[PDB]
Length: 416
Image 1 (cartoon, rainbow, N blue to C red):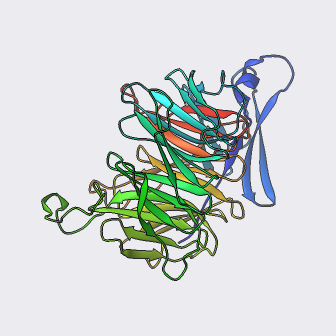
Image 2 (cartoon, rainbow, N blue to C red; image 1 turned 180 degrees about the horizontal axis):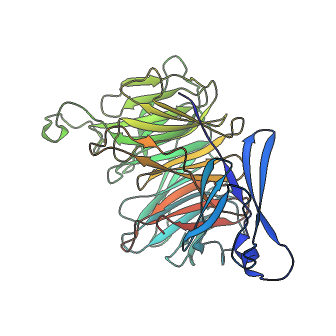
C-alpha cells in the first residue's frame, strides 16, 4: 500500500533572483529529498536571462498563477505556492506555537507564544491587544469560540483559560490536568469543551462553573499521553435529530459527538462523548507517536494521522484494523501537524516542510483520496510550521495561515 510523497524545497528568494536581470549566469536551486541521506539539487538557470528558465534536460519550471509555480524534475511533479501576506511583518519578535481565526463580530487572528503571551490581531494583522503572561508557560493551543467573542487557551502550565475579546478579561480558568495540556476541542457553541493532556487524559469541561464533568482515558493505559484530539459528529444508521435521549447534567450538545485522540504510544482512540464508551482503537501500526490527527471535513468516517517517523496515514473508522492509505513524508523525521481544510490536507514535517495535499473524491464523497503525486509546497525561508489555520474569504476559496518560531506568520492563497 505504502507510497512515498517526494518532498521539494525551492530557494526562498527565487523571485528576487529572477528579477536581477544581469549578465552573469545566476541560478536558484530546487532541492528534492530522496531519503535521510540524499538531496537532488536542481540548478534552475534563469537563462531566458531575466525570466526564461533552464531546468535541464527533460525538466520544466514555469509560473502558472500570481503566486503559483510548477516544476517537473526527474519524473516527479511539484507545485510551489508563495506567500501573499507576511502577517509577521509588523509584529514584535516572538515564537508562535498556536493560532486561530474568527470572522464574526470582525475578522481577528489570535497567536500564542512560547512565553505564554496571546496576541489579538485584526484583519490587517495589526496588534489590537496583547495579553502578556496569559499563561506562565508556552501556549500549546488557541481556539476561538464560534461567537468570536471569547477564546480559550491551553498551556504547558497545565491549565486552560477562557478570555473575553472585548476587555481581555479572564472569567474562567480550567484547573485539573497534571501535565501539559496539548489540545482543545469546542463542542457546539462551547458550553462544554474538551482538553487533552500528556497526563494521559481527555477532560470534558463545563464552562459555566469551570469544572470537569468527565475524564476519558485508555482503560489499560491510563498514563498514555494524548498529543492531539478532534471532535466530530458520528455517522450512524439513526437520525440524531429525532433522538429522545435525555440531557446529561451540565452537558450541552454532547449527543452524537465523538472525540478521537492520538496518543504518544501511537494508538488512536475514539470515545463517545455522550455515552462515555471507548468505541474504537486504531493500532500503533508504525510503532511511534501519533503527533497530530484531523477528521475529513466532508466525510467523518475518514481521519488523517501524522506520526513521529514521518508516516501519514488515512484511516477509515469503520475498518480500524488497517489504514486505507499510507504515505511516507521524509521517513525518519516527524510529522508535526496535520490539518484538514477546504478539501485539502495541510501537513507540517521536519524542520521546514509544509505541504498541501489535495483530496479528491467521487460524486458520493465515496472515500477521500490523497493526491500524493502532485503535492503543493507552501514556500517559506526554511520556517518551521507549528500550526495551520484556514481563513475563509467571500471573494475566493480562502487562504491558509501558518505560524511558527522565529516570528513566522505567513498567509497563502488557496487559488491562483
